[PDB]
Image: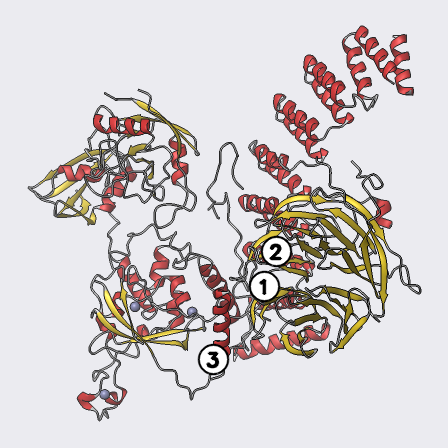
């Protein structure tokens, strides 16, 4: 407005990154 | 051992003499990867 | 010379493929083929060889170790991180994978967030050397409240008199005397309260002799009343001092 | 921790001999009139259950018979052996009438579906095969085990096919697609015996490491029955909740199914002229009355155990 | 009326404080505040997820073409020059056609001046632009949605 | 039982020794009508292709994570035992 | 000893619009395991039809797995989205995919990709389509829009070439002179066309596309002011400002109808280069097409 290969990291609740 | 190496050297000499003058349903390992198994991708990598 | 080198490489690859096809389960042929492919500077060919060998038998430690070492010896750091992530998620009980992953991500990687990755190992309740190395790693990263939580989880997960003595020494060396006294009180209340171990009482008496000799004499008298030869030696040391 | 229910102990009361090889498998006729043994004598013997008299002996197998089962809804007797052949015997004429063929190696066991009349066999070529009974057509080839599949179990509820193999893995299969569904890798050694509870929708798996109780259908881990550290070859469960684990060293352990509490250790003796190394339980089965336990011991004997009615709760107290 | 300057949205990716363009679009900001108060944009999965162009969430239909706003049925997209889909952290509505917009919020970290005239911008992402850029960098299927579903846990329209 | 009977009938009909449809095509680049007609198989006619082409076995399913109890390290007295 | 390529038996063939013809009612023939694949050599369901009135009775050549792998037609071996050879599309997008050439490795790779597709949803040209999201670089300039029916023309009568076609006008084959045999365009290996290696049609279209500077611009000595012709009084400065707003900040946007030129300049060199490349005979605003040059 006024300004003008990896994978998807899944995190559930406080669980740091679903592996 | 040495006799097979001498036979291979004689075959290479005959091949160079014929080049200076089928595939038997085989697999050529020097042309490409024989059974290409790609590594699994995850969480990283930007290739090279 | 290029055609002779191509014929030599074709003959070596034909003998390696014939040795693979003769005995599939022998992994030393796979290791020799992968090392010969890496010695000729063919990284993706050796990666395909290692992936085929892991598809043949994924339970071997040395296949993962050699393929991660081949990834780490080159500049493929993210490939090595993917290899270590796969090796951790398939075989969590092998501690050598964890140790080499932490040395790769700590020395070469130099990432503190790998400690969070290390907390994944703390889900698995490992042996006490993992806890000791994590205590020394948190000391090397200059964190003492985090190391206090680490040692509290170590005492809760692996309770031992040597573990409580190491907790007392770590709380004394981190200049928390009230926390050390509370840890010694909790160890006296829980660890060997009725078992009469007579070793955590000696450490509590040594901490009190560092603190105040009247409480050390009271602790030595309580240890002599609760009880061996070491308790009598500690009582004689408290009476002599 | 609840107290386990008191089970009365068991005692040996008859020993039947007459086989000239290792008795590898025992099956019981569903009307409880007779039972049947397969041996390394390449013979299949029908024995009377009550009197113990040898009713019949059938030849025709060329190698060691590894598995024998009796059909509950057909007058058929299915026998698998080390000769890479599965035989369907019509009992109506005591002759082999069907030959299921196609395994590349020795067949280590077989099981019948109780409702569909389809056959499943596990063999040493790392495959299980699912055969239609009437057409003798292998409708599926379950593969995915990397070593020899030691045993197979079958049930009507989902999942239908349970396989335990020598590569420390248990595979819960799907019958209609022929694909695996659940892989359990908790065992450290070869899974040689699996047994299914008749009513609690649970099962147990046997390995030299431990015995593991699980929960159908997801295969979630329930309990770790520890102790009895020998090569367990067989596993059967009573309808009353008694689990019998038989080992290759001859020792037998009896457990409560719920608490996992071992209440009896039975190490029987051997045949009169026999080595101490020839002590080992290859198979064991309860009868239809759930009151006689029949074991196929490695000294070419069938040993039959009965309940000891004279024992009471204070005479044999439950520890802890 | 309801003219909040900035609101907060906590989701699985993180917590983002997004400014609302109530100076140029007061009715759309009031409809967005009423949808955040009623929980219309909270709990709904990301219906539209472009390849690092615009990530749209809060649509109740889930297909990217439906959804209902606080004004009733569909909302007319009245675009203004003060609130344009340009730069990084632009908050707008992923409208498939003209004069048909729901209560869904779309965060764009790239230039979207072609779709800026056909949609009304709700505001700008003052905070949490990196979380929206990390959410929009995930690969999606042909239906502009991946296998995993990401929604909004809580929404606070303060102001 | 129904699915297995379908599989048995398909296997036997494959092993047994020996109408025109209408479909709507959307090319996605308007719609077309296609009359699906199967050509008549010649009964007087041998198989066409060699089917004895052996290739090595493919990759299996991706491996399961390995639960274990923590490993008891054997002593050196156990090693010469 | 129990691995072999499975036979691909499926209906609904994947064809181009051009090879399918123009009639909405097509009479269609299907053989279950009629011929082999021209690339992966597996048997497959062979579809045959006449696309029109005087066409060739075109039939499918490659199997459905290869055509789903490379996203091409089963007969024309050209791309479904654009009607281009796969060498041109691989030069446009990505040429690091490749395929084995030896028959055992080709059969093994095709069996692995077939198992991957059958374990997938069923109709997806792997992750290569994920690399095909970036488009319209230069391939849309030379892509055909009309259905080129002249490749459904029947073959040349070889008896008429020797002047002995006794059928005359009854002969369905073409009674016209063939192409030049000395021309290197006439070689056309099918495996070379599938693998995208030294295809002369692809080389000729790449040479044709390289001679069209539709994205060159840069004719000013470090000056961002570029003139777009063809705008006139139909296109004003509002359309130029709306085009330059996607690039960021524009230094100057103006339109002059005396020379019919739109002067566009940006404060950034990359934004001005993107605005000059977007307006170089590819931009149409307010019914006026603009061609970018120096001004
Ligand atoms: Zn076509
Ligand atoms: Zn093909
Ligand atoms: Zn002619």
Other-residue count near label 2 (Cα within 10 Å), few / some / many at <14 / 14–19 / ≥20:
many
Asked whether the beta carbons under mark 1 and mark 3 sit within 8 Å of each other, the answer is: no
> With D235 as the anchor, is D267 left or right in this view?
right
State which quadrant residue E120 falls in: top left
Indicate the secondary structure of the residue bearing disc 1: strand
Q: Position of residue D21 (x, y in %)?
A: 82, 70
Disc 1 chain ID: D
* Vertical comparison of G15 with E72: above or below: below
Q: Position of residue D81 (x, y in %)?
A: 71, 71
Q: Nearer the viewer, residue G20 or B19?
A: G20
Q: Position of residue G59 (x, y in %)?
A: 32, 75
Q: Residue F49 has which mark? A: 3
Other-residue count near label 1 (Cα within 10 Å), few / some / many at <14 / 14–19 / ≥20:
many
Query: What colour scheme does the image use?
Result: secondary structure
Asked whether the beta carbons under mark 3 and mark 2 sit within 8 Å of each other, the answer is: no
Do callouts 1 and 3 point to residues on the same chain? no
Do callouts 2 and 1 point to residues on the same chain? yes
> With E56 as the anchor, is D75 left or right in this view?
right
* Vertical comparison of E73 with D236: above or below: above
**For mark 2, what is the residue?**
D171
What is the C-alpha distance between the residues marked 1 and 3? 28 Å
Q: Earlier in the sequence, mark 2 or mark 1?
A: 1
Disc 2 chain ID: D
Disc 3 chain ID: F
Inspect this view and state whether residue C13 appears: no
**For mark 1, what is the residue?**
D142
């Amino acid at each position: 407005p006024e300004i003008h290969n990896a994978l998807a990291i899944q995190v559930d609740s406080e669980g740091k990154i679903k592996y | 051992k040495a006799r097979e190496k001498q036979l291979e050297e004689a075959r290479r000499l005959a091949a160079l003499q014929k080049r200076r003058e089928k595939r038997k349903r085989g697999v050529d390992y020097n042309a490409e990867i024989p059974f290409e198994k790609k590594p699994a991708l995850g969480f990283y990598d930007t290739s090279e | 010379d290029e055609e002779e080198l191509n014929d030599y490489k074709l003959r070596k690859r034909k003998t390696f493929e014939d040795n693979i096809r003769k005995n599939r389960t022998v992994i030393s042929n796979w290791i020799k083929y992968a090392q010969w492919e890496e010695s000729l500077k063919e990284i993706q060919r050796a990666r395909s060889i290692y992936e085929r060998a892991l598809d043949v038998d994924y339970r071997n430690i040395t296949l993962w170790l050699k393929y991660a070492e081949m990834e780490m010896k080159n500049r493929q750091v993210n490939h090595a991180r993917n290899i270590w992530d796969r090796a951790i998620t398939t075989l969590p009980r092998v501690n050598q994978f964890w140790y080499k992953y932490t040395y790769m991500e700590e020395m070469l990687g130099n990432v503190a967030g790998a400690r969070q990755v290390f907390e994944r190992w703390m889900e698995w309740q490992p042996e006490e050397q993992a806890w000791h190395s994590y205590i020394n790693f948190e000391l090397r990263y200059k964190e003492v409240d985090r190391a206090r939580t680490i040692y509290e989880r170590f005492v809760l997960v692996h309770p031992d008199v040597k573990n409580w003595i190491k907790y007392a020494r770590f709380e004394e060396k981190h200049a928390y005397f009230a926390h050390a006294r509370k840890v010694y009180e909790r160890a006296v209340e829980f660890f060997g309260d009725e078992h009469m171990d007579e070793h955590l009482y000696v450490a509590f008496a040594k901490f009190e002799e560092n603190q105040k000799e009247f409480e050390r004499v009271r602790v030595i008298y309580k240890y002599a009343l609760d009880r061996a030869q070491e308790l009598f030696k500690n009582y004689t040391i408290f009476e002599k001092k | 921790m609840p107290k386990p229910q008191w089970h009365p102990p068991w005692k040996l009361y008859r020993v039947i001999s007459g086989h000239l090889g290792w008795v590898r498998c025992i099956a019981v006729e569903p009307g409880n009139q007779w039972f049947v043994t397969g041996s390394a004598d390449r013979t299949i013997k029908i024995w009377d259950l009550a009197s113990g008299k040898l009713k019949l002996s059938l030849t025709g197998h060329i190698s060691t018979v590894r598995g024998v089962i009796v059909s509950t809804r057909s007058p058929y007797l299915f026998s698998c052996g080390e000769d890479k052949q599965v035989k369907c015997w019509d009992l109506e004429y005591n002759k082999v009438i069907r030959h299921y063929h196609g395994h590349l190696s020795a067949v280590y066991g077989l099981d019948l579906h109780p409702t569909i009349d389809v056959l499943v066999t596990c063999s040493r070529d790392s495959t299980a095969r699912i055969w239609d009974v009437r057409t003798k057509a292998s409708v599926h080839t379950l593969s995915g085990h990397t070593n020899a599949v030691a045993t197979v179990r079958c049930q009507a509820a989902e999942p239908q096919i349970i396989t335990g193999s020598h590569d420390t893995t248990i595979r819960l299969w799907d019958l209609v697609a022929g694909k695996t569904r659940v892989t359990l890798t908790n065992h450290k050694k070869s899974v040689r015996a699996v047994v299914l509870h008749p009513r609690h929708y649970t099962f147990a798996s046997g390995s030299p490491d431990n015995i593991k109780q699980w929960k159908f259908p997801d295969g979630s881990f329930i309990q770790n029955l520890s102790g009895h550290n020998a090569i367990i070859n067989t596993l059967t469960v009573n309808s009353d909740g008694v689990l019998v684990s038989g080992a290759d060293n001859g020792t037998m352990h009896l457990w409560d199914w719920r608490t996992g509490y071992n209440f009896q250790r039975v190490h029987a003796a051997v045949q009169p002229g026999s080595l101490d190394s020839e002590s080992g339980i290859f198979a064991c089965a309860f009868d239809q009355s759930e009151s006689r336990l029949l074991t196929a011991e490695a000294d070419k004997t069938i040993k039959v155990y009965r309940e000891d009615d004279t024992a009471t709760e204070e005479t044999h107290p439950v520890s802890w | 009326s309801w003219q909040p300057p900035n609101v907060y949205l906590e989701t699985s990716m993180g917590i983002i404080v997004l400014e609302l363009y109530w100076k140029h679009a007061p009715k759309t900001c009031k409809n967005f505040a009423e949808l955040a108060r009623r929980g219309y944009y909270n709990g709904t999965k990301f219906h539209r997820i472009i390849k690092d162009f615009m990530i749209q969430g809060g649509d109740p239909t889930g297909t990217g073409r439906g959804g209902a706003s606080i004004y009733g049925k569909q909302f007319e997209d009245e675009l203004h020059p003060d609130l344009k889909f340009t730069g990084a952290g632009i908050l707008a509505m992923a409208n498939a056609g003209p004069d048909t917009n729901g209560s869904q919020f779309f965060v764009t970290l790239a230039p979207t001046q072609w779709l800026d005239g056909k949609h009304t911008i709700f505001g700008r992402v003052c905070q949490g632009i990196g979380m929206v850029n990390r959410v929009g960098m995930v690969e999606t299927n042909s239906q502009d949605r991946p296998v995993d579903d990401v929604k909004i846990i809580k929404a606070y329209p303060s102001g | 039982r129904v699915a297995l009977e379908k599989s048995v009938s398909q296997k036997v009909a494959a092993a047994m020794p020996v109408p025109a449809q209408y479909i709507r095509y959307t090319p996605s680049q308007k719609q077309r009508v296609i009359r699906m007609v199967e050509m008549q198989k010649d009964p007087m006619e041998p198989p066409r292709f060699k089917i004895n082409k052996k290739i090595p076995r493919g990759p299996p399913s991706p491996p399961a994570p390995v639960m274990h109890s923590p490993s008891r390290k054997m002593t050196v007295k156990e090693q010469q035992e | 000893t129990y691995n072999r390529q499975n036979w691909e038996d499926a209906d609904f063939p994947i064809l181009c619009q051009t090879c399918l013809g123009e009639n909405p009612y097509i009479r269609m023939t299907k053989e279950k395991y009629g011929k082999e694949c021209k690339i992966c050599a597996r048997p497959f369901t062979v579809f045959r039809w006449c696309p029109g009135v005087r066409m060739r009775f075109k039939k499918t050549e490659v199997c459905q797995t290869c055509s789903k792998l490379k996203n091409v037609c089963q007969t024309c071996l050209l791309d479904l989205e654009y009607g281009l050879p796969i060498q041109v599309r691989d030069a446009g997008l990505s040429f690091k995919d490749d395929m084995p050439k030896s028959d055992v490795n080709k059969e093994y790779y095709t069996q692995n990709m077939e198992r991957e597709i059958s374990n997938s949803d069923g109709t997806r040209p792997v992750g290569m389509l994920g690399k095909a999201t970036s488009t319209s670089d230069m391939l849309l300039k030379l892509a055909r829009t009309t259905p080129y029916y002249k490749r459904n023309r029947p073959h040349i009568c070889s008896f008429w070439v020797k002047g002995e076609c006794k059928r005359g006008e009854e002969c369905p084959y073409r009674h016209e002179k063939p192409t030049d045999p000395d021309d290197p365009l006439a070689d056309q290996n099918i495996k070379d066309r599938y693998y995208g290696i030294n295809d002369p049609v692809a080389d000729k279209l790449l040479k044709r596309a390289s001679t069209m500077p539709r994205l060159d611009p840069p004719e000013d000595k470090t000056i961002t002011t570029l003139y777009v012709g063809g705008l006139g009084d139909t296109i004003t400065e509002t359309d130029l400002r709306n085009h330059f707003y996607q690039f960021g900040e524009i230094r100057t946007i103006t339109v002059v109808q005396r020379q019919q030129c739109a002067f566009i300049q940006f404060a950034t060199r990359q934004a001005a280069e993107v605005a000059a490349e977007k307006s170089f005979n590819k931009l149409i605003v307010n019914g006026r097409r603009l061609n970018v040059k120096w001004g």
